Amino acid sequence: IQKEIDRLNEVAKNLNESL
Amino acid sequence: DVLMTQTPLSLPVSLGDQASISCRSSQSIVHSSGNTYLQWYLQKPGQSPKLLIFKVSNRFSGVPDRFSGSGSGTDFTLKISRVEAEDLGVYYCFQVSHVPYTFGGGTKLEIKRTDAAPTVSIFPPSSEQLTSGGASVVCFLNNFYPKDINVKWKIDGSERQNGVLNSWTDQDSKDSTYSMSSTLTLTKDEYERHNSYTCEATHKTSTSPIVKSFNRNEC
Amino acid sequence: EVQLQQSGPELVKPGASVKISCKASGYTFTDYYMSWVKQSHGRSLEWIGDINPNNGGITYNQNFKGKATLTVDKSSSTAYMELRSLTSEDSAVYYCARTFAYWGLGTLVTVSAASTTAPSVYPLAPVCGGTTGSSVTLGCLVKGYFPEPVTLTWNSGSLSSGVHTFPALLQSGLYTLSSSVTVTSNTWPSQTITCNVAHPASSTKVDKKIEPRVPA
Image (tube, rainbow over all chains, first blue to last red; front, top):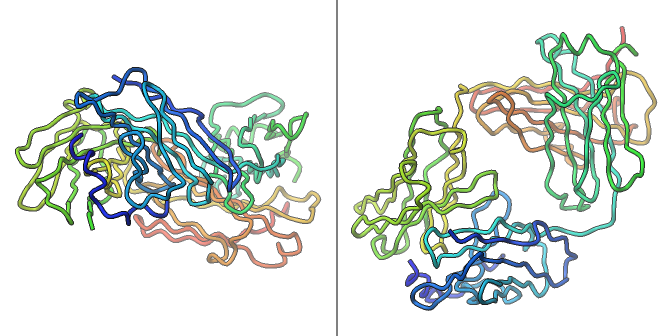
């Protein structure tokens, strides 16, 4: 799972904008 | 297991102010890869946690830049450079470096405002409930601040504790107060055997307890 | 987009078992672990375990061994949790999550011996008599229902300013909630004020007018 967390900012910066 | 200790439990702030939240691990949380997998979440009421920061300081996706995470060793910190209304809720840290992964107990971000005295109302059992064998006496303590309040029930001058249920609202979005409902439940038979019923509250806005009472025989 | 769709709310008897599901879409199910997290009392979070969908290998939280069993079905991109020998302590929201970054909406599990139970709804008019100020407060008591939720409105929702509806609490395996409303004293009793309660699970629907207490 740690290797997955390493790659979290592969996603576009369009999530969780309303936090 | 790694204990994650979050402070403060609750953090009252003004909108537009900076805020910081602390997370202490009981031991080092460095994974065997050398990285530290400390995440921060915001959870809003009735909603799922939302990831803000991962691996101590990396901002996730489109999370606003006013959020940032930092720290090292056993000190970790989440900062909000300018608190906005959509940021209100509970913040959690979470370590995924050592199994079992563990969460902090959360820090609730709330609005600070001036003190406000509770408006207290007491309600005898409804005549309809009496026909059923139970009797609930309800006391509302509405629109007060801060949230700390102590409520006591008296029956004919004697404290009654068994059968009391207390429920609090979340902070009001319009005036930032809290409210609470206190219910004393007894059997109809017991209720009819006593005369005076008193809801007593202590709050920081008054040096005396706020008393509201009625007599079952007054009408 | 990444989406985790979890099964609906579960009402389970003490000592029974329940199986919860999480369907993944928007990414390749077998390229990522799936994790499960418990949340009780709307606060404390606890990690339950991770499953590798590719080979079915699991990393459990030691404290949930025997309580929770994790499985997957690759052909439907679904992860499963089965909770065994349920007790009150297992009443919680159970989340599935991918990389602890994409979370499902959660599945509420409530453990209770109660059957579906309609509420008794009681209007709370002020103490008989007395003096009135510039405002007056009325109440409504919704006692002994199961499961959650009830819906409660005042004058069919028209009356919303000055309302406080309090979170339901448990009492004898059953829920109870209450609600107060504060209006100008020129408004009541001259105008009608009614609390409207609905309990879908029992098809119960009750409107109670708040009427002044009379002596005789």
